[PDB]
Image (tube, rainbow, N blue to C red):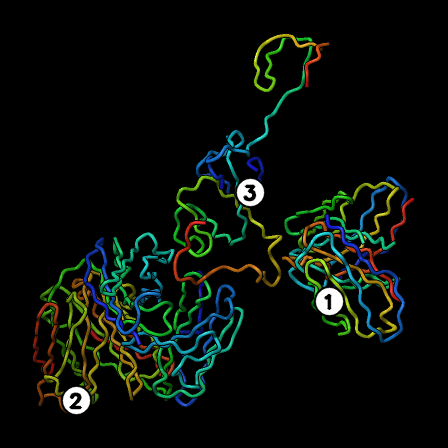
Amino acid sequence: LYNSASFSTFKCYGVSPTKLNDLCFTNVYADSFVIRGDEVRQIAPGQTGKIADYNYKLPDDFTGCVIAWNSNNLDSKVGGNYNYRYRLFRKSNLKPF
Amino acid sequence: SFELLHAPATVCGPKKSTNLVKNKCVNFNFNGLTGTGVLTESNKKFLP
Amino acid sequence: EVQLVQSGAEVKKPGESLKISCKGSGYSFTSYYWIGWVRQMPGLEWMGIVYPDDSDTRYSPSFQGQVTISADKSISTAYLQWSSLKASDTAMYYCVRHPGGGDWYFDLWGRGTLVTVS
Amino acid sequence: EVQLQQWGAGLLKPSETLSLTCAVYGESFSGYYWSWIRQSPGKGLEWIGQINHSGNTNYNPSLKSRVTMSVDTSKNQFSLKLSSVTAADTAVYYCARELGHDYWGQGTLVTVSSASTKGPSVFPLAPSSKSTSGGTAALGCLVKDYFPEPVTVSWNSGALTSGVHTFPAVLQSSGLYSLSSVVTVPSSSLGTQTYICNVNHKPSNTKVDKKVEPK
Amino acid sequence: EIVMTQSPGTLSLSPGERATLSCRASQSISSSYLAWFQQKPGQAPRLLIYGASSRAPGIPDRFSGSGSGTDFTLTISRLEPEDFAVYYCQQYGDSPLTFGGGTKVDIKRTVAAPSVFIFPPSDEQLKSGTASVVCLLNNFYPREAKVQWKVDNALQSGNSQESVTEQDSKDSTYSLSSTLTLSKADYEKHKVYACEVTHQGLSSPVTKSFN
Amino acid sequence: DIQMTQSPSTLSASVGDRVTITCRASQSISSWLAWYQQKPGKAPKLLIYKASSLESGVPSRFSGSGSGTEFTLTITSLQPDDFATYYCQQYDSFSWTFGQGTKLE
């Protein structure tokens, strides 16, 4: 993953990316989802958007990291992809995870 | 998300290795035993 | 009328380059779809697809035409880029467009051409 | 039904902090989002943010770095703080419920300027002789150099209320305001009647009376 | 930030007619989540139409809305005297609520002609060291007008400002006052001064001059 | 890849009769199905997209059903012009594999 080039963002928070290989953990969780371009800066521990509060709240004690890449070829039509939806209205903020 | 160690870990990266050169003096690591020497074929029969 | 049109049939000796061009017409916003070829063996085989705007290609595992298909901006020429072949297999092609964006079924077909080798 | 009552300071020096409060009556304060909307004469309606009783805040990304919101559940109030205020923040602020669509506050005007309170001044005017020859003339008093916006002007001690034009105040380079109040009269009335212009500036507690006479 | 753009801000039409207002969004609006607000002077905006098609409770039936995608329009069947206000768009289908620019509606009538009643600078202001002269206009329906100052037979700009009153309740006209400031030495140096009035209704280029 | 078995084969029936064909899947796919019409000497023609959804310009006798693995195409009334070949297609994974096909006469 680290040596790939299609990835647009690869910042890591608790662990440096150069020495990811030599570290053993109990479990690895991969959360996958699609968002828009301007909204990708909100996936970090501590944010105040509509995705960090109503869709994908992250804990402040985060240790993995986030990998985002543009996919305009797969998810696009000359009309629109109305199959991707987001939570716009809620009554309270989501708890982490 | 890398769930940190609370029980003994079971996931981490592969360990690389080199070729097996014989009949030359070479520093060697074989699953953690380290040393320098000349490695040659043997007629010893270790149990499994 | 939207249409994918191809040239005439052709036959040539082994070791000679074979190119097939499928032309998209009738609708605007071309090169924003996914264009590709399907092997016509009814006696049903899909090969890779190409996105003209960014020249991105996928390829089926079993079949591989080894084609870097590119389309010019003005003439929208999504011609097959195949400079070599082996006479053992017959690469019978129908050119097909994709709606894209999840609707990955084959919607627009072409009449196609008969390819004879050797 | 929900009744919204808001208050807060209106005059602010540059680089100060703006504080406004809004109070809710009539319905439940919990289980709702309360929003602040700003309206400027040069921009238009703008949405600042919103807060609910639990303390969760939604902010406009443009103002997110300068806007803070607080809620007091005991007395059913919510408040807005806008730090490092600038002259571009002069506007009318409303407190509304959710996106609006039902109920809005009355609105609080906020003026941000680095000028101190000053008293208005009246400049005399004289109609031209050509206006007298034509048949109609205009008599007007010009008020200048008062900083706080609200000022009242009347003529004939308020008796003459026909044809009175009071143009809106304009802001000058020095940071003060000025306006003019005019009345149209026949030229025949000239030379036989005496007029009067009266100005009342409440924030400076100033009352000025001028006797307007022909030419 | 879905930026909304509206039809021309000012449009004039006689009462008892139909009105159409356009509204465009830079991007598609989800589920036609568009709302129309009406604001009268001195009051907070009031909702008229939600969902781009429906009508809010208590709203008269003469307001209608229709549109989709990135194009919407509001229609008023008959304009009562109270229907003259400012109308705004609002999209609530995305994260930050965005409002439109706003469209104003006026009252149409016959074209009038401005009357000019200039006042020369007073002595008291000259004692204070500032000079003010006012090209004045009175009673003209078309708000669009131009006045240009001529000092030493040359164009003057950047030193004068204009103030226009609101539309009258019954006369439906406008009054404008343009004030130009010049230096005392400059005002003494030159002998001829003028303000020239160009208006579509009044063809003659009246150049009101004085010394 | 996806291995998809078209259990029905060359079938004979009179004109104006119910006909049902099935196209079993190796593993469940969430109604990501396409039915294609084929005639001898003619290019393949798109018939049905998204499992049970009729395309414009197609007679109403064709209908689709099935969720996950039991995908089926049913024609209520057979026609002389309906004697042709049907092709399966799936687009769950990127390796888009067709079906074996069925013959009608």
Q: Is residue A35 visible?
A: yes
Q: Nearer the viewer, residue C29 or D37?
A: D37
Where residue E60 appears, as percent x and y from the top left, is 40, 85
Q: Nearer the viewer, residue D178 or E77?
A: E77
- Where disc 1 sits, the SS reads strand
Could you confirm whether marks 2 and 3 are on the same chain? no
Q: Nearer the viewer, residue E41 or F98?
A: F98
| Residue C31 lies in quadrant | bottom right
Given the image, on which type of amino acid does mark 1 rest?
Gly
Question: Chain ID for label 1?
Answer: F
Q: Which residue is mark 2?
A: D187
Q: Is residue D130 visible?
A: no
Q: Which residue is mark 1?
A: F64
Where residue E181 appears, as percent x and y from the top left, is 21, 66
Q: Which residue is mark 3?
A: A7
Indicate whether E58 appears above or below A36.
below
Question: Chain ID for label 3?
Answer: A
User: Distance from label 2 to label 3 (Cα)?
Assistant: 83 Å
Question: Do callouts 2 and 3 mark residues in contact (Cβ within 8 Å)?
Answer: no
Q: Please give the name of the residue rendered at 39% of the width and 62% of the height, measured from the top-left corner.
A: A91
Q: Residues within 10 Å of mark 3 (few under 14, many from 20)?
A: few
Could you confirm whether marks 2 and 1 are on the same chain? no
